[PDB]
Length: 212
Image 1: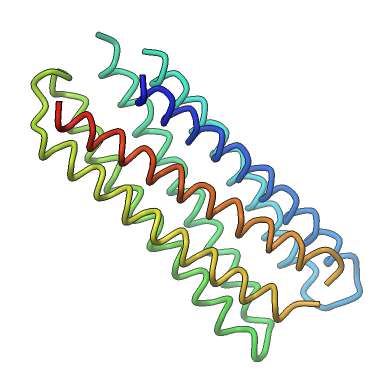
Image 2 (image 1 turned 90 degrees about the vertical axis):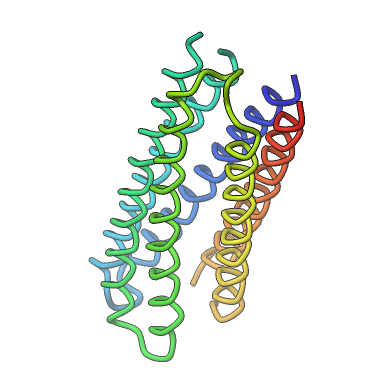
């Protein structure tokens, strides 16, 4: 009911985020056309973003299968695997971002902090996957309400971390002036903010389910 709707809203927000990442990848490739140094690092960062976008669309499909359906346990484990794969792609993205930042001056610090934030996000997603694999081994009617409330809290903390990431990308955009890079960064920030909202709505559905 409300759970299926919250899971599908989240999958939709993940697919929109993937599209914003693909736009940013294109901006970075155009930046790599020779009008500024560090062509190779820009191209590598662009490729990592396209790989991140592919992992997000795989995660969205996993959520859609969960929303549509005794097979609940299997679907949760598939979801946890997709999260672990997304975490790996985030760590690779952070690695490429650090390499790019080595080429900048005043901007190097904000780019390095951004990469550190992605590394912390990856760690939080691995912990979420672990919690989901635990839940998957408990029959849905035997799950403790506190197990559901802890999951909702974890999603609310993830939303806060994405809003902080969005704020840092907005500040980066203000300092930029690319081609359409500024517009691609602002759009990405808005997609992360929408994702954070969809995570808060899912947390609400879990807290509602915990009360039942």
